[PDB]
Image 1 (cartoon, each protein chain N blue to C red):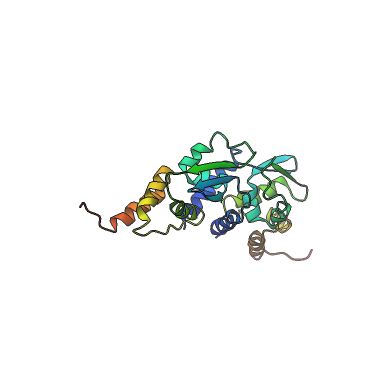
Image 2: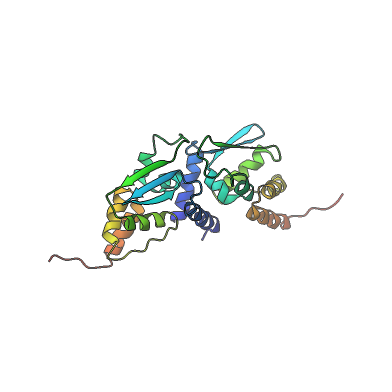
Amino acid sequence: SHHIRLLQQLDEQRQKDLFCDCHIIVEGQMFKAHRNVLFASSGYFKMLLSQSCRDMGEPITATFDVFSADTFTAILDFVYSGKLPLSGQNVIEVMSAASYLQMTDVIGVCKMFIKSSLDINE
Amino acid sequence: FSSHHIRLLQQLDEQRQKDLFCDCHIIVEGQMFKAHRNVLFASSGYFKMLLSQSCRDMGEPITATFDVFSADTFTAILDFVYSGKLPLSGQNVIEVMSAASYLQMTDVIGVCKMFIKSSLDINE
């Protein structure tokens, strides 16, 4: 109960640029988020923010040209909700983005959704 | 139930105990508590007001103070914030209710008033 509420509240903050010390540029589009949540949710961010984790200064600005802004949206939406919206169109790019960002849970979800479909060679 | 929510709070509780991303210091009866202002904002109405104005100012860490409750009382309150588990008893139930009220934590207040129904109080 308290766990669900806290995450519902934090998702609201990032959507209002509240306490957002981390900017993320993916294909020009910018995503605002919390440096302590990304650190707890992604191995990539656990490494990128590791050194500058007690430097309260300007907000830290990450960049990505390795996945699409739509792909990263589903990734970031999952971080603050625990719900990943999958489909044939997104399942692959989400798995890639989750791997690059070191989000093992999202990868496992994809390989389960992938096992729930059929792909073959031409 | 939700492992994603449980893990995140287990992870955030560890961060504050290692002064990681701690932009809020709290001095209660000399003892200092390090925590995240975005979590306190989400968990307490008092902090939702104290930090309201300075909510997009990424600068020096904000340092709050309290002489209205004990450091032990604030620990149980703060430990609940990062765990969701509040251990109540006759010794703390009143001071926790006071601290929860002052901090505007309606859920903690209701929990105390429920444990209060689990004891007996009468006039002397």
